[PDB]
Length: 103
Length: 103
Length: 103
Image (tube, rainbow over all chains, first blue to last red; front, side, top):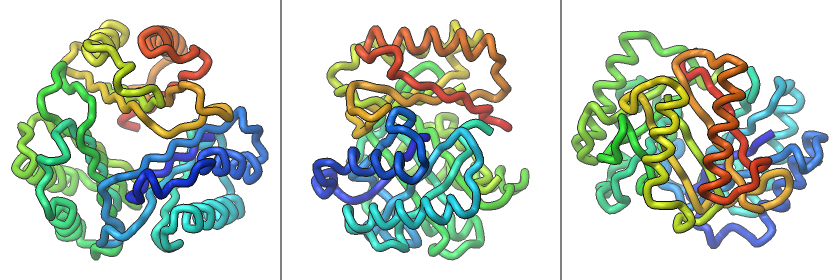
């Protein structure tokens, strides 16, 4: 699958090893080997979310299958927590859309 | 909903207050409170449109519902006009795709 | 149609004339006049692909029709080869998704 993150936090607030960590995390969460994963992080964006430009993140995960409700819940929790902790965004400001990359 | 704008106009040609204005506009147009809106503007892009790299904009609006034909018309008019006026792009060079964010 | 390319190769590794070339290529491949084509190239991205941050490219082609299997094959070959040659990415590191822009 492919995980895209669009964020208004500065490029310098992104830790060394963040793309590697996130990559390993998705590999754990999805049960897919790192070989089937792509991560794309885009910092320094001009964005408003729920009315303000406080730190936020619009993300999307694209898979070649339909994710189930339990997976959605488990992915969002894991992914929002990772993003809020490492990039310091309030959990309620990280939004994730799931797309059936082949549907 | 979420409105994404990809444009080749420079970051400095984007006015102070543009994200706030656009945000308020979408809130008016859609009847949704600013709380349910996200705007993402990406300037300085390398893009050609109808063959040239004259100023242009590729945008997409993502909603959790199907937009009707009258809404599409009303959204495009309002949104293209706002973008052409504030960012100085010819109206025929602003393209908007509508996605049913949950379909 | 619209062809989007997200790549981790530097902006300076992108040749003068690349957007014009790619544009003409899509016009040839699809049988559509340059007027119906848009190209968007985004370099300098933070991305991992199959586990590493070696040069790669995540792309998507959006059309107002369903592409057939022969077209997919023909588009991928042409497009991956163009991208690998001009931007120096290993062919197995260029991924292209096809979307029915109006479906």
